[PDB]
Amino acid sequence: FMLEMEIKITEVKENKLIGRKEIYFEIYHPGEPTPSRKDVKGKLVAMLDLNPETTVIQYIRSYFGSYKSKGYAKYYYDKDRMLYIEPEYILIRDGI
């Protein structure tokens, strides 16, 4: 097969007041450049059984010295809440 990216969930926090999951994870992308936010979102959603419409990658940090990247995503239980909280540039950037 071809080299695949792998997500490791390191932490999920349930934010009751805001109504979201706060999700920290590692991406291992061996023999490959850092993957796109798009592909990273696809794996995370698949992995956690999440609606992609309300899954918001905030950042993905990479390191020149390794094939592991570290990301932060928020998942909103309600779309309209997402829209009130998240800046439009972030939502646009993330395919939302």
Image (tube, helix red, strand yellow):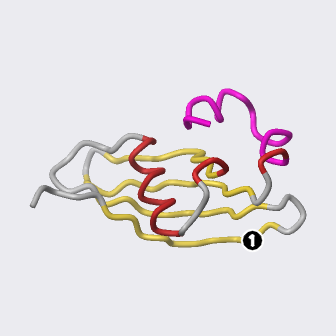
Residue kind at label 1, given as amino acid type: Glu
What residue is drawn where x is 57% and y is 54%? 72
Q: Classify 33 as above or below 74.
A: above
Identify the residue at the far left of this view.
1
Residue 77 image offset from top left, x and y in percent: 76, 60
Q: Classify 27 as above or below 12.
A: above
Q: Classify 61 as above or below 25.
A: above
Residue 51 image offset from top left, x and y in percent: 61, 57
Disc 1 crowd, CA 10 A, few/some/many (<14, 14-19, 20+): few
Answer whether residue 83 is magenta in the image. yes
The rendered magenta stretch, by its main secondary structure, is classed as helix
Q: Classify 77 as above or below 12.
A: above
What residue is pinned by disc 1? 14
What residue is drawn where x is 83% and y is 44%? 80
Instruction: Write down the region rendered in magenta.
Output: 81-96
Classify mark 1: helix, strand or loop.
strand
What residue is drawn where x is 44% and y is 52%? 42
Q: Nearer the viewer, residue 80 or 35?
A: 80
Q: Quadrant of the C terminus?
A: top right
Q: Nearer the viewer, residue 1 or 33?
A: 1
